[PDB]
Image (cartoon, coloured by chain):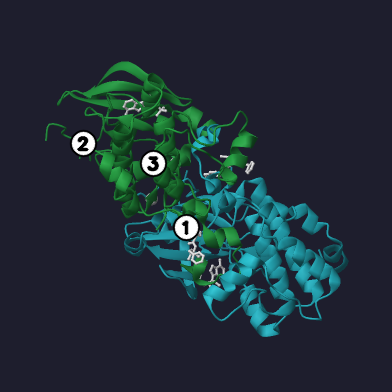
Chain colours: A cyan, B green
């Protein structure tokens, strides 16, 4: 397979054209194990800049048929630059391996934070939703839809700032296709999986999970969860305040066009009453 | 911008390593114009084999932001090998142009055949639907969905058989994403635009257009066409027979999961009574 991506492979001077080489990095402890290779804490040798190096094995990527997914993830993420989006500085590859040079987020995942605290107060929740909506507003200005927002894909920086990670399901949103609607089925004309409103629903699920400690459609079988999502059937515990209910209910709409714009989330009075941000 | 695709660029002995070059081809008359270049009749010089050379301009592709769409089109189509799918033998590129080396379809488009005849008899129609269903069964076996089937995209081979062309909107649709439904909106769970059933609707529209000479949701505004498609509002002129009505009505279902399998189209009693294949 071709590992020539439309993504940077140029060496970066982190203190302030040569391409990356494995010899540029002092490889330290494993940070995590992925399906195709691990993530290591690493340092670029010249600058001593601390980063995360994700090592993936080409043989394994091709056997699984996920190499074009990796290509798209790298091409998308490496062109996003925002303080609440995990940076992908570049990539390179050698005879057997692909290497992703990533921002190191030192304080783990929001998934872990929720495990530890069970639920978040309204200030932490509103701050995190502010950070996510800012990150997603930036994505949508680049016509990028993330499509896999959930707590294990939210990493924490050293000041506790949220970092959206995992662009493996993202797409670059918007011809002769639509010039002629006559031959298109309803689902091609609507194009809902390519609508930026996908990510607004996930923001509502997160806001609920942050406050309650479980997501609103949780069930012990897939079929019951899908049923409740389809009916938008969920309930609030008594302790969820009316302002929080208003925002969450606005976001969890089956019809994506009824969901709010991200600016309306950022400007919601419950968010501005409670955010540190 | 990278023009390294996971698609063949090796020289082929059409009578029966070295990469393609423009000087391998004699160029003939222009076959057609597109917004990004032109298509020419061409001939590979050693074998004298007739083909089509589609020439696209890099500057126009990159300005329009469609270069990754072309990459996907070439990657998908060059790995499909079926007598009712237009072959893409390989590609190459130079400082300004991308070249696609295509099978030449000498009898033109089904679109032009409809202009000439107005409408098709049942035997011609059923034979075309069999060829199309065969091609789509092969595609779906390769986990490819075409998503833009329409008469302009159906070319005609030397024996008058259909050749599906234009894979510009196609997707290869073979997982942590669905591991948890809890954070996915309904449109991501359902994934309708990634369902192979997309192409069964268009088969129904085509069957109608072939018999009637107008597509079933035709309207004089796009908004009205969309409303008719969304509402599945269509009717038949009186000459359309009961068997054809049954097939078309079975294909044009709003819910993709209610559309038939391709085997049911190929074995439909109207199809087998009328198809020469
Ligand atoms: S074709 C009409 C058009 N819809 C889209 O562009 C959605 C779409 C389709 C195909 C894609 C894609 C996105 O990305 C990949 O391939 C449109 O006009 N949409 C707006 C609209 C929707 C519903 N009603 C009216 C207007
Ligand atoms: S996540 C459930 C799964 N749906 C999909 O895989 C659709 C999909 C999602 C994301 C994509 C994609 C396709 O292609 C590109 O990214 C599924 O099991 N669907 C079938 C199903 C739906 C509803 N209930 C039961 C089964
Ligand atoms: N850039 C990073 N900084 C810190 N930890 C990470 C980084 N990327 C991945 N991880 C962690 O390593 C584990 C495996 O990563 P992945 O294979 O990318 O899912 C995950 O649980 C992450 O929490
Ligand atoms: N492989 C081919 N064989 C014959 N005609 C073609 C071929 N490819 C494209 N054409 C014609 O050239 C015109 C423009 O092609 P396109 O740019 O693919 O839309 C269309 O009218 C097609 O009829
Ligand atoms: Mg590749
Ligand atoms: Mg490219």
Q: At which x and y percent is residue B227?
A: 62, 41
Residue A58 percent coordinates (x, y): 35, 60
Residue at mark 3: chain: B
Estimate the spatial distance between the alpha carbons at disc 1 and disc 3, rounded to whole Å: 21 Å
The answer for how far apart the CA atoms under marks 1 and 2 are is 47 Å
Q: Secondary structure at mark 3?
A: helix
Between A227 and A165, the one nearer to me in the picture: A227
User: In the image, is the residue at mark 3 within 8 Å of ligand 1 by its beta carbon?
Assistant: no
Circle 1 crowding by C-alpha within 10 Å: few under 14, some 14–19, many from 20: few
Q: Is residue B91 left or right of residue B35?
A: left
- Report the residue marked by disc 3: B244
Residue located beneath label 2 in the image: B18
Residue drawn at x 54%, y 72% is B180
Disc 3/disc 2 C-alpha distance (Å): 51 Å
Q: Nearer the viewer, mark 1 or mark 3?
A: 3
Q: Chain of mark 1?
A: B
Nearest to N terminus: mark 3 or mark 2: 2
Q: Check the picture and name the quadrant holding the C terminus of chain B.
A: top left
- Report the front residue among B103 and A143: B103
Q: Secondary structure at mark 2?
A: loop
**In which quadrant of the rendered view does residue B272 lie?**
top left
The residue under label 1 is B257
Have a look at marks 1 and 2 and say if they share a chain. yes
């Amino acid at each position: 397979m071709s590992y020539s991506y439309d993504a940077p492979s140029d060496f970066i001077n982190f203190s302030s054209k040569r391409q990356w080489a494995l010899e540029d990095f002092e490889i330290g402890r494993p940070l995590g194990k992925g399906k195709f290779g691990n993530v290591y804490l690493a340092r670029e040798k010249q600058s001593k800049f601390i980063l995360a190096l994700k090592v993936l094995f080409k043989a394994q990527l091709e056997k699984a048929g996920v190499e074009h997914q990796l290509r798209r993830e790298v091409e998308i993420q490496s062109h996003l630059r925002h303080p609440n989006i995990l940076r992908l500085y570049g990539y390179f590859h050698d005879a057997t391996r692909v290497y992703l040079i990533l921002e190191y987020a030192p304080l783990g995942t929001v998934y872990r934070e929720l495990q530890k605290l069970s639920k978040f107060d309204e200030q932490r929740t509103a701050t995190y939703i502010t950070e996510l909506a800012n990150a997603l507003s930036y994505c949508h200005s680049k016509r990028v839809i993330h499509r896999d927002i959930k707590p294990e894909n939210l990493l924490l920086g050293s000041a506790g700032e949220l970092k959206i990670a995992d662009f493996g399901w993202s797409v670059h949103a918007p011809t002769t296709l639509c010039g002629t609607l006559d031959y298109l089925p309803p689902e091609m004309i609507e194009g809902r999986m390519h609508d930026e409103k996908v990510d607004l629903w996930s923001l509502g699920v997160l806001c609920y999970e942050f406050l309650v400690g479980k997501p609103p459609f949780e069930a012990n079988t897939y079929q019951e969860t899908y049923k409740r999502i389809s009916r938008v059937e969920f309930t609030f515990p008594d302790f969820v305040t009316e302002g929080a209910r208003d925002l969450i209910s606005r976001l969890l709409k089956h019809n994506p066009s009824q969901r709010p714009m991200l600016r309306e989330v950022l400007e919601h009075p419950w968010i501005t009453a409670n955010s540190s941000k």
